[PDB]
Image (cartoon, rainbow, N blue to C red):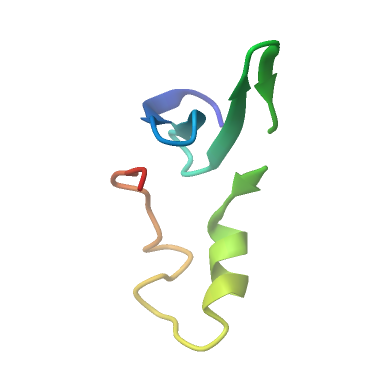
Length: 70
């Protein structure tokens, strides 16, 4: 995506997360020499992920409201 709607930081693991308008997530490893990445989760990844349940996570319906680091 296009813009980065939200930014989140995992304090415990020094990991950066970015959520874009489109709903793609990117998690950079924060290192002394810079950011290392960027792995991504997308709607496609999620679909593959469920592999057992689906509907609310429909393509049309699918959108991400918020992301929180654990």
